[PDB]
Length: 264
Length: 264
Ligand SMILES: C#CCN(Cc1ccc2[nH]c(N)nc(=O)c2c1)c1ccc(C(=O)N[C@@H](CCC(=O)O)C(=O)O)cc1
Ligand SMILES: C#CCN(Cc1ccc2[nH]c(N)nc(=O)c2c1)c1ccc(C(=O)N[C@@H](CCC(=O)O)C(=O)O)cc1
Ligand SMILES: *c1cc(=O)[nH]c(=O)n1[C@H]1C[C@H](O)[C@@H](COP(=O)(O)O)O1
Ligand SMILES: *c1cc(=O)[nH]c(=O)n1[C@H]1C[C@H](O)[C@@H](COP(=O)(O)O)O1
Image (cartoon, rainbow over all chains, first blue to last red; front, top):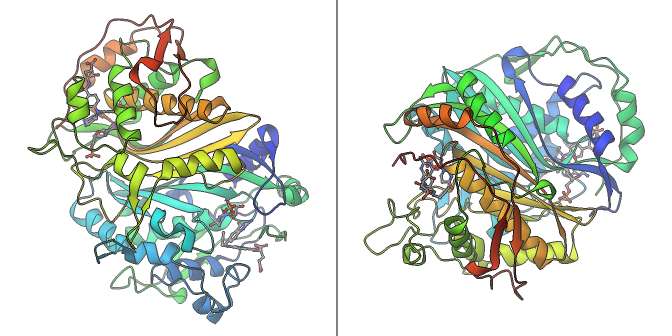
């Protein structure tokens, strides 16, 4: 899509060569923002085929507070394979912090439920937030949260959300992330009887990997196509009852997919 | 400042009537981002008389992990009197989380010192972050962190930082917050022998209080003037050893000041 392609070109134009953890090398810019009016279509990149299926499973995996790739493998999702340990454990990452942030005094904060309640009984709150950046458990996670801080907002019956992604692999990761939260907004919006608003994406270290250049140029040479439409065949009792079969994608006519090696 | 006046003007045209935890009412938008290249000058609003004293004391206060308004009240800084308790306590706010974020297992993380080391030994890191949004303590705090999460970044010998402010009172707080972080950047920079880069400001609920409309139109009629230059007269041996008398501002020729009420 346009915002995405423009972000690619932006990095290409004013990015700086920078070494990195993986040792792969990147071209990066710091700080960026784009918006997607969910009412214009589900934001699923078209300049290359994307498997919305793997995205759904990763999200449902979070909403259950699970952090062992076992469930993912149960559905053929290999996105955690290069970092999980022998027991398929990544650590107290996304899921654990989302449903059960451990307080030093014994409590466990279920943030998703907190936000839900706020959206229903206090949509005006400016503190409707979910954070995966729990400093106290960083060292235990197999990898630091990329999408680490998001906020919800409601106005004129529309639900919006902005994500803060401290680190972002524009070519391989961004498309997953955008679709992820966009998806979460629909679900929340459905449970809270609200319409979908905008999904504001904000980034920190927005980079393009040295070995993703050729593919980026290939995608950037393709013309974006109409955005598809998210279809939820059923309204579950809670935001914790969605299953992969409840989601449907219509009108998605993406360009051929493009493979690229991930930096471990 | 141009960017600030553009944001202020945007809230007017596109803003939406909302209601806040303070029966004051507001006109807000959700999600915005501005960029301040510190190389062009210290970002201290000029279309309104301001001063660093309070901002300086607060930051030094934060850097010490202090959360009691004694230091502030001492030098006559009232910014936090309307919310502290009979003992001057605000609870575990900003400074507490910055210098001693409590893990779930009896330990405390000094995020500042951590970042200090990350910039000196691992500048390419995409995990140099500081958060005050400790979910397990949000209910022990007198007030929820507005400037709740920020990140650092290095490139070509220049330190840059981005702040995620989930709640922002455009007329009153923004000018304070902006110059506050800018200052921290210059401080971190000196402490690491780096030069200052960009201060990226990102906001969630960006509102304009309904009882600030008059002073907003007044400020909008003024022409921004050249930004001033910051001078740190001494180089402490620690980012925690700075003294109020270390800061100077040269070339600040602002328009008259504008008084406004604080939504409690
Ligand atoms: C984001 C996210 C979730 N994750 C988590 C995750 C973990 C580490 C990461 N590390 C790096 N350097 N890039 C990422 O974006 C990244 C993302 C993913 C991880 C890998 C792939 C991946 O390589 N997909 C390939 C191959 C697809 C396939 O197997 O069919 C692709 O071409 O998309 C996708 C998602
Ligand atoms: C941010 C921050 C710290 N704080 C914290 C703080 C707490 C609650 C808030 N509440 C609201 N509605 N907006 C804010 O910006 C805000 C700021 C401050 C609190 C008050 C003032 C204040 O009343 N300033 C006046 C007078 C300043 C002067 O003496 O020149 C002003 O109009 O500037 C400034 C900062
Ligand atoms: C992390 C996973 C995700 O949800 N999205 C991504 O974009 N990323 C990328 C960022 C970076 O290239 C890598 C994480 O590495 P690091 O922790 O920033 O060193 O995956
Ligand atoms: C909080 C303090 C700060 O450092 N900067 C500010 O702009 N804010 C403002 C935001 C909001 O108008 C008010 C706090 O409101 P709430 O806690 O989000 O309801 O202070």
